[PDB]
Each structure stands twice: as C-alpha cells, then as structure tokens.
Image (cartoon, rainbow, N blue to C red; front, side, top):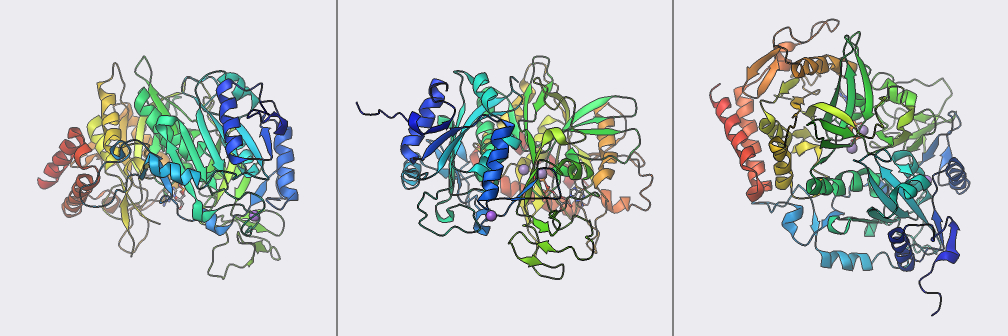
Length: 612
Ligand SMILES: Nc1nc2c(ncn2[C@@H]2O[C@H](COP(=O)(O)OP(=O)(O)OP(=O)(O)O)[C@@H](O)[C@H]2O)c(=O)[nH]1
Ligand SMILES: [Mn+2]
Ligand SMILES: [Mn+2]
Ligand code: NA
C-alpha cells in the first residue's frame, strides 16, 4: 500500500532479492526494528575487507601496524572488556532446562532469564538502535563448507570491527549464502547500542553501551541477541554464543558434542598419527598445546583448532571432530618465541590485535613477549598513554587478543578443513592446581573420565580455587546435569570407540611457589605417554585417582633434576579433602539432576582414598 516493509532502497551492497526467503525476512524484520541507514550484505571478498579496514583507519577506529604485512590495532573503551557473565543469559520456558536448581546457593553453572523478562529487555534496547549506521549482514559457516558437522549463521551487526573479525574467525560471504539455500541457520543479532546522534560521548572511538549490555541466547528460537558490547565473545557471535552455548544445545538434541577444546594431531617416530582434544579453562594454556613445538626428536604436532571442538561419533564408531572456527582468537600476553613460536609466526601478517601496546616503530608489545626493544624504541600502552617498564599498570590488557587466520599457522594440520573431521583417540582435562594433583593421570573408564571432567577445578587469576567443569562453566547451553547424562550416554551408542580420558596439571608448585614441571614444548613427553597408553603399552601404575606413569615411563632426558617424587606425589590427606569438596559442590550445584553414574564415581573415589 505504501512501500510495504521493503528496505531495498537502503541496500548498498548485494540484493535482498537474491537472499533466501528466511534470510530476507530476518534482515528486513530487524531493519524495520533497528532502523539502520543502510544495509550492506557482505560478500567476504578481499576488496570488501581491505576497504572496510581503510575506512576504520580513516575514522580512528583502528590503526595500521606499519612493521607488519596488513596488521591492525584496535583499542577499546576500557568499560567494554569488564566482567559480564552477569549480563550473559539463556532464555527457555523452564529455568531447569537451562541450569540445575541448586540446593543451597545461587547457580554457578549458567544464568537463566524468562521469556517475559527478555522481551521487556529487548524492547528497551533494540528499537531504533542502528539509526545513522550501516547494518552489515554477515553470512557465515561454523566449520568447513559442506561438512556434515558444519552449521550456518547470519549475523546482523552495526560494527565494522565485527565484520573484519568474523571474516578471520569464520568462513564468511557469498559462498555461504549459496551453500545455505533454504536450509536452517542460526539468527545472530548484534548492536553496539549507540544510535546516531550519540546520546553519550564516545570513548576511544569505540562504540558501546555498558549499562544496557546484555548477551542473550534463545536455543528454542535458534537465536542469539546481543546488545551494548563491541568486544570479543559479545560481538563476534560465532566465537562462544554460537560455538558453545547454542551449539551445545543443538548437540544435545542431535547426538553430538560442542566443547571448549583444542584439537591437535601428533605423529610419532614411526609415522603413526593420533588426534587428541583438550579442555582447559581460560589462562590454562590450550593455545600453547594446540600449536606446540615438541622437544622430543622424531615427534610432530600439528594444529586443527585451539579453542572449540564439535565432535560426533560416525557410523564406524570413530569420534570425528571438526574445528568450527577459521582462525585463532588468542590471548596475546604471554605469547613468545619461548611459549608459542608457531603463534609468533602466524600473527605477523593479516592479523587484528585488540588492546595490546604499540611500539614507536609500529610493532606490537605485551607482558611476556620476551623480546627486548632497541634503545630509543618507546611503547604506547593499550590506554593510549606513554608507557615504561617501571610503572604499575600493564602495557597490554591482561586478556587482550590477536585475531589471526588459521591457514597461516605453519603447523596447521593437513586435515584441519577435512569435511569428515578427524578421529579423536584421547580427551584431556586440566587446570591450574598448585598443590596435590599430579602431572598426568588416566581415567579408569568412560564413566570415571566423565567424573574427572565434572570435578575440574582451577586457580582463579589470598588465592581462590574454583570449579570449572569441562572448562565449560561460562558456556553451558543447558542444564549441566543433563550435559553429564549426554556425555555418559555416548557409552551406550552402537560401535562407539570411546577415547581414553586423561587429566593433566602443568601448574603444580613446590613449597616456595616454583613450578615443578617446565611445560610448554616439554609437554610432548606427556603426550608421548598418552600416545603409548592409547596403544595399550604397559606403562601405567594404578593409584586411587587413576593410572599414573610407572617409574621411568616418562622420557625425562635433558630435563636434569625434575623433582618426580613431589610432581607425582598423591597424598591421602589432600585427596580426602578434595573428594569432600567435590561431593558438596555437585550436591549443591547439580542437586536433583546429578546422574547416578557420577554419584557412583564419587562414592568409588572416596572409597579408594579411604583405603590408602
Ligand atoms: N607453567 C605453564 N604455564 C603454561 C603452560 N602452557 C600455558 N601456560 C600459561 O597459560 C597462559 C596462557 O593461556 P591462555 O592463552 O590464557 O589459555 P587458553 O586456554 O588458550 O584460553 P582462551 O584462549 O581464553 O580459551 C599463560 O600464562 C602461559 O604462561 C605450561 O605448559 N606450563
Ligand atoms: Mn586460547
Ligand atoms: Mn576459549
Ligand atoms: Na579505539
């Protein structure tokens, strides 16, 4: 009767008419709601990318890092990398489907919001929120195009930084739209929450709305709706919202697993290769392991992924894993030639850095780079101030990131994009435990291994030790007890070849606070032991917590005087306290949804400890 709800006049790249019907409805419906000035349907081309970077550069949104080949630096409003799992929620009809109902306290395992409450929140945020801005339409694949394990999303965003970063971290553009056709997709809606004219002053040329920041997941509607943050997991909606929260619920429904795991391939000196997955929390070194440079001669490690694993048993019973990401969104501080040489070589081109320091010669700098600068070279911190080594403040934000293409990693695995995925033979859990937990132990069974994941604890970074089951505490898409049952159910599947489960601790300290294990490339010696155990080698000693390496089973040559007594010590007094703490945690936090098999493993461990 007038123009309908036809936004064709506002399209500045692409065509609404060429979009699949349901994608068009999603775009136009949100264009009506958010009132963007323009619509840009991303094609994923190199020209689109380069021009958007130059535009952001011209506006002061990012700076070019002149030392490198096509690298860039964004400095955020410091409010936009504050703690916001308080503002991260999942909407379902029933709270219990999202989190177990705890016995004593508040839940640590997720944060539910009612549908009613969410609709009020949404109505208070999104209407007119993109006024004066371009709505970018990002078609993206999580996983290799045409992998039967891949899933597709469409992200609408008003942030060019999100567009640039999603090109790196996902497969993005016209080829995705063509692969999608009329199939299902996850609807991803994002706004920085700063319509023009700006109602509040812009800090550091970084649009955000901290007071209204809210990151919502609606698994029954296949929707992620995120408002007010331009940063990381809040804005790149593939990264955690899709990769873990939505995907874990899809996995539950469909019979697969979505996990906070690296995936690596390891080849021995006789050419035999195995793939392993490992779940460690933030600050516990997944990215270091995934890209490891092994010290043991004749061994090779190659990287499939450093953060997310989507895993499904195939008809032959093999546990096939893909990396659903297209890049590495890695913590910058602590990355050096020493700790991650392969990362150092990946990130010197075509990489976007956020919240690190800049050197006067146009390079990057951060705590732990271990790379001295020439006299006269000066440093600008992530707060855009002159910075000196003898100051209180760090030069980079402690969780600042690089965002780099996976294809550039010099040890990227030749099957990192194989659509069928890679066959996983081992799953590793671990965190930071300064006391009591040995370097490595092996679980006694699948059920025991699921308990080991469930019981994971890690020192926060007096000190505090917190539970982080499966390294998924921030990320469960649904009730953690039901997740445990889902894991346990894999054992009753036809022909499943259940991988061996291990627990590691890189972080045990002696009584003066010194690390007992050197770690990093030396962890290859632990992987050698795991490799042998998967192969059935008689290299294990039974203990109350699981199997540990026999005396002399680990290759310790070249390590000198490693204190093996302390590094492998298992104390009854420590483990008595441990099991009690785990018992109380699971009772409180999982309560009526704790599977029988987990409670049984808890009872069994308590019993074996009692007989020490
Ligand atoms: N002592 C020791 N520290 C390690 C080792 N591997 C990694 N680290 C430490 O782990 C930290 C880096 O881990 P992150 O990159 O935060 O961990 P991540 O698991 O990749 O975290 P996300 O990217 O947030 O998922 C640094 O403090 C490293 O020094 C190791 O083998 N030994
Ligand atoms: Mn990482
Ligand atoms: Mn992570
Ligand atoms: Na900035």
